[PDB]
Amino acid sequence: HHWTYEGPHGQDHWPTSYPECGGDAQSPINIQTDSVIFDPDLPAVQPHGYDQLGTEPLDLHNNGHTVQLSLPPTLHLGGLPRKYTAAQLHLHWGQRGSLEGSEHHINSEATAAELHVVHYDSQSYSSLSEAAQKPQGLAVLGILIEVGETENPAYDHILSRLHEIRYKDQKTSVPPFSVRELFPQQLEQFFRYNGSLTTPPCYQSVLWTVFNRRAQISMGQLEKLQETLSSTEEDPSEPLVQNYRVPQPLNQRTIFASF
Ligand SMILES: *[C@@H]1O[C@H](CO)[C@@H](O[C@@H]2O[C@H](CO)[C@@H](O)[C@H](O)[C@H]2NC(C)=O)[C@H](O)[C@H]1NC(C)=O
Ligand SMILES: [Cl-]
Ligand SMILES: [Zn+2]
């Protein structure tokens, strides 16, 4: 009953146990810039005070599928059709030695890792779980991550505590830092489109926003994230790597772009 990324119960078999996973509007997708429909009327994606996470420790845990940080309900995402509220944040990366770990592609090119900031329509629904299966219920932000030559301080707020949550299900708290700094510096350029969650149940309620600019972390930072967490509760451990879904069929969907 426990899905994994590759293997007997890998993403290839999700449709079997999770019908929605074989939906017509699944994510991620390979964004082809030539097919992108320019939309000068798309308002800017503006994260309201994502540099102010309050005072309380944030929860950072291990799913055996990814490292996930928790976010206060005070974080509000503007610029979309409805008002969305940040709920969680996590990562996707490739195995040790690979420089391809993102889920979304750009003209068939994948980056080293991808950051997903999951939001939910708190204006039309009570909770995130309520919106998880509502049309346009969720709103995710996809930040593609490349390997730069300088150390990224924004990400150490998470990479510097990965050893505390090595095994699946372990958790911990971290001093609240500026999440805004995890996003690329310029947010003007982005692609919008209707997608789904990239893990079972694969609900098609996500209104995606994949930024065009990328975020960079040292090759050292990428290795830490790649070789620290395990997917098991206890030993023998098993590298929690290759935790990304492969690009899915676009099935005649329009991918808009702010630029
Ligand atoms: C995601 O899907 C929704 C619904 O199919 C799209 O919204 C529709 O947009 C048209 C014109 O753009 C309206 O006439 C419809 O009424 C909208 N549907 C409803 C019921 O809200 C939306 O454009 C898609 N998002 C993107 C940008 O791909
Ligand atoms: Cl089982
Ligand atoms: Zn994700």
Image: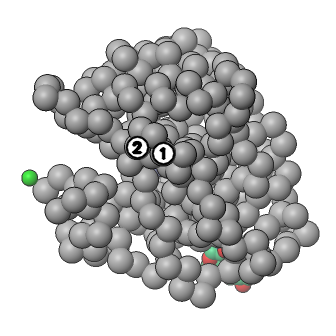
Disc 1, ligand 3: is the CB inside 8 Å?
Answer: no
Identify the residue at the far right of this view: 40
**Of residues 45 and 236, which is closer to you in this image?**
236
Q: From the image, tell me which residue sits under label 1.
A: 98
Label 1's element? loop
Q: Residue at x 45, y 40 (%)?
A: 97
Label 1, label 2: how many angstroms apart (C-alpha)?
6 Å
Q: Residue at x 76, y 55 (%)?
A: 212
Compared with residue 146, is residue 226 higher up or lower down, i.e. above or below?
A: above
Crowd around label 1: few <14 · some 14–19 · many ≥20 (10 Å): some
Residue at (81% x, 37% y) in the render: 185
Q: Badge 2: few (under 14), some or many (20 or more) residues near its Cα, within 10 Å?
A: some
Residue 141 in picture, x, y percent from top left = 63, 50
**Badge 2 element:** loop
User: Is 48 rendered above or below residue 173?
Assistant: below
Q: Position of residue 45 (x, y in %)?
A: 77, 51
Q: Which mark is residue 95?
A: 2
Q: How is the rendered protein coloured?
A: one colour
- Residue 18 visible in the displayed image: no
Which amino acid does the dot numbered 2 rest on? Gln
Whether the residues at callouts 1 and 2 have beta carbons within 8 Å, the answer is: yes
The quarter of the image holding the N terminus is bottom left
Task: Please state if 17 lies on the left or on the right of 23 as rendered.
Answer: left
- Residue drawn at (72%, 28%), measured in percent from left and top? 149
Residue 17: where, in percent of width, then height?
Answer: 20, 69
